[PDB]
Image 1: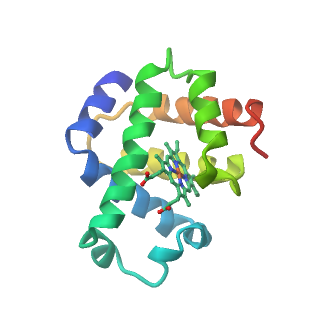
Image 2: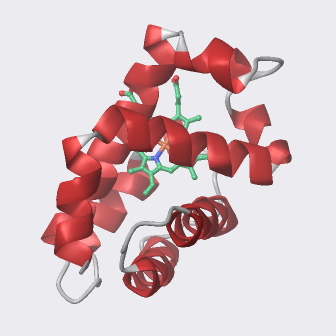
Image 3: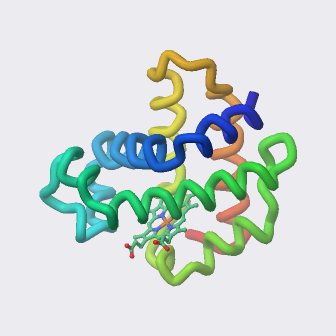
Length: 137
Ligand code: HEM
């Protein structure tokens, strides 16, 4: 289920974080603009780079903490509020996060592993509706 998925992801956080983030960028290439440091670089160029790995690690670590504090895939308001009020997210809209979760769910469905893909879809929808409530456009 969802809790075991969080354990799987956490067990190999840097690998899953990199692979899902690159799935996102490659599915929605206009999103790369938000990451000036990653423009014009292959997946392997990025996987060799400690700072790309460090970035993806820190993002997915917080995503797993939000997921683990959720009840029935409903995230905490306080956690949606952290994500809206981070300086780093000042330019973003809920569509940026929707696209990340579509990529994550597609990644999980394509994986061959027994991820609870539908729970991640519901988590992402519930997180988008919480970001909107906390004032994201
Ligand atoms: C649930 C989803 C997300 C989480 C948990 C999250 C979390 C984070 C965290 C923890 C950082 C700081 C990384 C560090 O300290 O090195 C960060 C930075 C950032 N995030 Fe997010 N993020 C999310 C979604 C997004 C999305 C969808 C976008 C854009 C499409 C975005 C754009 C950024 C940018 C541009 C930075 C600054 C990167 C840098 O300075 O190197 N994030 N995010």
